Amino acid sequence: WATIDVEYREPAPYVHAQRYIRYCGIDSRELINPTTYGIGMTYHCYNEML
Amino acid sequence: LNDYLLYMYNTRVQVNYGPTGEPLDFQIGRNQYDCNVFRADFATGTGYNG
Amino acid sequence: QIILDLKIDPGERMDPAVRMVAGVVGHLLFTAGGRFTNLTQNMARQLDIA
């Protein structure tokens, strides 16, 4: 809802599928520490549910 | 090093990615220090000693 | 001369009951401006998100 799910990135190793699936607007490019990654982060569907 | 300056286990600082997809192509931190210079370049020796 | 900084270990960083009280208490215990400082630049950041 009012977000960018799919973003087409620069040419990928396999040239037939070069899409980036970003669930709820998370540009997950870095490695994840599960304690300090989701601090201060939200999206449009989750705010309009609260 | 691209998987070390981005695995943030303290509070996450901001990061602005470059246009390409090369490693160490970003600007990290609050004062936005350029991280492109630490890539190897054998005609100048830009990252390492010398 | 002796400043202090919070630990890294999860389980207490994910505990919302400990993390909420330790933000309220921390503003009444330490001095973080003016002349001297008991905290670190990084620790006092985690006591505002708390």
Image (cartoon, coloured by chain):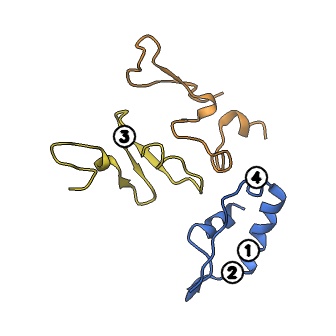
Say above or below: B23 vs C25.
above
Provide the chain ID for the residue under circle 3.
B
Residue at image position (82%, 62%) is: C18
Q: Given contact means CB atoms under 8 Å apart, are the residues at marks 2 and 1 in contact?
A: yes
Q: What residue would you read off at disc 3? A: B18
Residue B41's x, y, as percent?
A: 22, 42
Q: Residue furthest front?
A: B49
Say above or below: B46 vs C23.
above
Amino acid residing under circle 4: Met
Chain letter, blue? C
Q: What residue would you read off at disc 1? A: C26
Q: Colour of chain A?
A: orange
Q: In which image quadrant can residue B22 be found?
A: top left
Q: What residue would you read off at disc 4? A: C14
Amino acid residing under circle 2: Phe
Q: What numbered label is drawn on residue C30?
A: 2
